[PDB]
Image (cartoon, coloured by chain):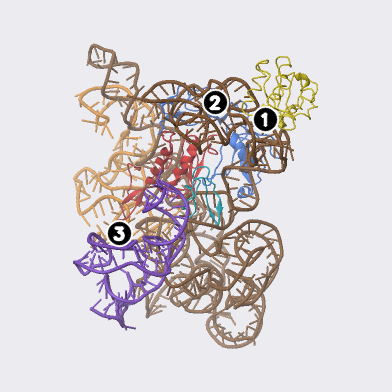
Chain colours: A yellow, B blue, C cyan, D red, E purple, F orange, G brown
RNA sequence: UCGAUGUCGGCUCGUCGCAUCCUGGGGCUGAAGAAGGUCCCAAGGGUUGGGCUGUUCGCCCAUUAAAGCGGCACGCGAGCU
RNA sequence: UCGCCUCCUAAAAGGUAACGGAGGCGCCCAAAGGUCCCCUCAGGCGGGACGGAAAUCCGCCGGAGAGCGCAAGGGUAGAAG
RNA sequence: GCUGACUGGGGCCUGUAGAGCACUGAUAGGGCUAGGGGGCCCACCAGCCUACCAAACCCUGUCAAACUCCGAAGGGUCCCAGGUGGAGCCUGGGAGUGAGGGCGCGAGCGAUAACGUCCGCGUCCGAGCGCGGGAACAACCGAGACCGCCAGCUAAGGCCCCCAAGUCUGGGCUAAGUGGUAAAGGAUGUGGCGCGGCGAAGACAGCCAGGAGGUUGGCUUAGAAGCAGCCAUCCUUUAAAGAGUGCGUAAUAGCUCACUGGUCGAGUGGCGCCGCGCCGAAAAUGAUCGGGGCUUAAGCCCAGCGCCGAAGCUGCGGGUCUGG
């Protein structure tokens, strides 16, 4: 209950620090598609548009404390959290739209988004991708 | 840092202990009336203030009385406190032992290094109101040879204390 | 190690289990098979 | 070994082991420590017996104290010689020890050790014993 | 116990006891096989002939699977020498 | 070893045991005795030609640790010295 | 002819248990410094100071049959009282007995051995081997037997049976026939307490997933990837990751891991107390708690009611010895 306030409180200064925050679910991914999904989303960003496979139970509060909702639909399982802080939110969500559609992944393994403050759907992870 | 004592009336001391309570006695120039508290409630406290801080009481009398042990009879055998004592704190300067805590890392350590802390407390007089807690020592130059003592230490403004000044306060001997 | 009047844990994988009416100890390498006697 | 250097009488009527301890019950020195539970006579040899083992478990480590001291003269008659006819000569020395009698105490020795030590340290000893640190050992103020 | 309970050794005849010398069993092992080493279970049945010494015991010779440790008034004299 | 004196043992009166623990006695002194008049230590720390670490000195602090023929012990400078 | 034992209060004698170091010694560690070798140095030898032995000084800690600044409880003695008992005091005639024993407590010897042995206090056997209890049993518990009764109540010890009297009543533990008798020392055996670590921002169990970078740093009389060995003792791509507890290799590759996403989605792990039970635990004709048998007992622990049971005490009668 010590670093739980060190990790969950480190999950909102970057939640309330963005303009393109995703959080799909990733399963069956080796040790080469992870340093390839962020080696490919930080060249048009640097040290800001990282690949965060965050926490799910630490999102029912890493989201309800700075006061929010419309989130009870995006991480009910092993969910991530693609937070974009630098560079127009159009080179980390296109460099994010072809990082699950380039190795034979079905284009339905993501769970919406909160890119700039206005809920997100399933035809918008393909919309702000092309 | 607070205790509630129950007025001892004068009912079999053995009882109390053979009860669950822990007998004792508070006093000072003016007072001296048999008392008691519970065993357990006690320790938790002791083990924290023991006698280098000030224990305040309350009693059924909603009276908070500032004190601190003059002693504690023990048990010789199967150690575990027996009696206890409480010095009703006045505004008059008083004989209390300041808790000592040495700082820094011993010179003679890389080289033989095993520090002996002779007496890590001390007979310091002072207005009970103003009682610094721990007193800053040193080792940034302490060798196996003789070792600092008496009055080669800091006397927080207001503190005069009674030593000699003589009592070697500490030193380091040879390992094995 | 096998039968001794002082049975203990020798290593880490050792488990003190008891049975039949005596303390026992099993482990990875039989080199520990302890049995109160 | 370990014993006086002097004496006022060589031979001394043995006596008994009653309760109490009269002394030593507290710390007064070290960082942790051992305490006798049962009353008895502890032979010098037994004293060093551990003494060593100690320093042993901790090669060039902390500083030891063996707060006890033998100085009663252990008496034995000659192998086989029969009754009466004067008192056997000395054999060795002992240190009467009434319970709650701290015996030794380490210091500066990482507890883990200080402890572990005071565990074997006692295995040489002929009675149970107890491990401790510093508590109600404060007879300062 | 002295108005007596015969005092070593052997011979003979045994019985017992496990702390096991074989033989049967087991686990380890610095156990490859073999052979052993150490610990447990276990007396059911076995546990040799001679040399010297009064000797018990030893110390040798030749074998043996093995040549075991004790108790039984250090068994056994109304049984013997 | 055998009579005798001291201490412990001996359990707060006395005494009280062992082939119990540890020492002495089988003498001395005509002054080492009566008495009356005088006097004060041992040590410690300074200070002192031979001078240990104590001789005999000088100056302080020091009531008894000196002495009292001898064993220990009781006692004692308000004197037994 | 009321002093006796015993008891109260008065007044004192005294040096044990204990405890304490003030005197005699023994003491573990510290600090301190008269001193001395030594050096700067010449000198009637001033002084400065020592990475040496140490007198004593005090500190912190204790020890003692023959130590006591200190000192109980107790015991003794004397005064005033209580105390009419096979108490005392006194005189005279007779004794026998002067090997003792056991048990408890205080001490020596002994090995804090012995149905050992020697002394003190007390008890008992002796001579109370008459009774009861204790399996049997002089001395452990009951208890003082003049004699009788086809009477009553208890004491110790008992209450299922042999074998008199609760398969009696409550509330706890025990699972080994422990009880129906051995220790140290070991252990996730149970029962009642304790303090901390962390969770419904879903922990430990559960399984599909990641275990990265500097990287493999050097000093080497072979070489250091976490993966023989020391100093410095952190940063990078991070959901999480060192120069990694190791199964696992010669340096390695890896099965996997501290650290972690999380499907699961409720409590959960390593430690201190007491009861109580387990292993430790081998002896010599045939076993055994006296026996048979006992498992919410016929045990063990705390309660409560009640009996059984003596030769002790009552009822009754008789015998008897002192006194009035």
> Disc 3, disc 1: CB below 8 Å?
no
Pointer 2 residue: B135
Foreground mark, 2 or 3, reads 3
Q: Nearer the viewer, mark 1 or mark 2?
A: 1
| Point 52% across, 42% down: residue | C12
Position above or below: G154 against G191: below
Q: Using residue C14 as the reference point, say whether residue B13 is left or right of it.
A: right
Residue matched to label 3: D80
Query: Callout 2: 10 Å neighbours few (<14), some, many (20+)?
Result: some
User: Disc 1 designates what residue?
Assistant: A4
Which chain letter matches label 2? B
How far apart are the alpha carbons under marks 3 and 1? 77 Å
Residue at x-position 48% and y-position 40%: D116
Inter-mark Cα distance, 1 to 2: 37 Å
**Residue A109 screen position, x and y as percent:** 73, 28
Q: What label does residue A16 carry, if any?
A: none
In the image: residue D75, left or right of residue G180:
left
- Residues marked 2 and 3 touching at CB (< 8 Å): no
Q: Secondary structure at mark 3?
A: loop
Mark 3 crowdedness (10 Å alpha carbons): few <14, some 14-19, many ≥20: few
Badge 1 crowding class, 10 Å Cα cut-off, few under 14, some 14 to 19, many 20 or more, is few
Q: Is residue B167 visible?
A: no
**Towards the viewer: B118 or G72:** B118
Image height of G147 relative to G43, above or below: below
Q: Viewer-nearest of labels 3 and 1?
A: 1
The answer to whether tags 3 and 1 share a subunit is no
Q: Is residue A90 left or right of residue E1?
A: right
Nearer-the-camera pick, D127 or F51: D127
Give how far across and how far down residue G60 sits, in percent.
46, 35
């Amino acid at each position: 209950x010590x670093x739980x306030x060190x990790x969950x409180x480190x999950x909102x200064x970057x939640x309330x620090x963005x303009x393109x925050x995703x959080x799909x679910x990733x399963x069956x991914x080796x040790x080469x598609x992870x340093x390839x999904x962020x080696x490919x989303x930080x060249x048009x960003x640097x040290x800001x548009x990282x690949x965060x496979x965050x926490x799910x139970x630490x999102x029912x509060x890493x989201x309800x404390x700075x006061x929010x909702x419309x989130x009870x639909x995006x991480x009910x399982x092993x969910x991530x959290x693609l937070x974009x802080x630098x560079x127009x939110x159009x080179x980390x969500x296109x460099x994010x739209x072809x990082x699950x559609x380039x190795x034979x992944x079905x284009x339905x393994x993501x769970x919406x988004x909160x890119x700039x403050x206005x809920x997100x759907x399933x035809x918008x992870x393909x919309x702000x991708x092309x | 840092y607070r205790l509630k004592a129950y007025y001892r009336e004068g009912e079999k001391p053995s009882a109390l202990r053979r009860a669950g309570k822990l007998p004792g006695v508070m006093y000072n120039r003016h007072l001296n009336r048999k008392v008691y508290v519970d065993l357990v409630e006690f320790d938790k406290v002791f083990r924290q203030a023991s006698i280098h801080h000030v224990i305040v009481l309350e009693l059924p009398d909603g009276q908070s009385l500032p004190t601190l042990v003059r002693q504690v009879n023990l048990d010789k055998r199967r150690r575990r406190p027996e009696h206890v004592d409480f010095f009703v704190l006045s505004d008059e300067p008083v004989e209390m032992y300041v808790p000592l805590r040495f700082v820094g890392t011993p010179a003679g350590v890389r080289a033989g290094g095993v520090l002996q802390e002779i007496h890590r407390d001390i007979l310091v007089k002072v207005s009970p109101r103003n009682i610094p807690e721990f007193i800053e020592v040193d080792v940034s130059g302490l060798e196996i040879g003789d070792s600092l003592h008496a009055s080669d230490l800091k006397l927080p403004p207001g503190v005069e204390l009674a030593v000699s000044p003589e009592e070697t306060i500490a030193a380091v001997v040879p390992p094995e | 190690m096998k039968v001794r009047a002082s049975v203990k844990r020798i290593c880490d994988k050792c488990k003190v289990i008891r049975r039949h009416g005596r303390v026992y100890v099993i482990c990875e390498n039989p080199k520990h098979k302890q049995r109160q006697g | 070994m370990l014993m006086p250097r002097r004496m006022k009488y060589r031979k001394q009527q043995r006596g008994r082991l009653k309760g109490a301890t009269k002394g030593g019950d507290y710390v007064a020195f070290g960082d942790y420590g051992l305490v006798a539970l049962e009353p008895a006579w502890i032979t010098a040899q037994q004293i060093e017996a551990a003494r060593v083992a100690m320093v042993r478990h901790f090669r060039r480590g902390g500083k030891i104290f063996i707060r006890i001291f033998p100085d009663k003269p252990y008496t034995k008659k000659p192998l086989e010689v029969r009754m009466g006819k004067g008192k056997g000569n000395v054999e060795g020395y002992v240190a009467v020890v009434k319970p709650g009698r701290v015996m030794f105490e380490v210091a500066g020795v990482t507890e883990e050790q200080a402890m572990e030590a005071l565990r074997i340290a006692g295995h040489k000893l002929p009675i149970k014993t107890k491990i401790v640190r510093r508590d109600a050992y404060d007879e300062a103020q």
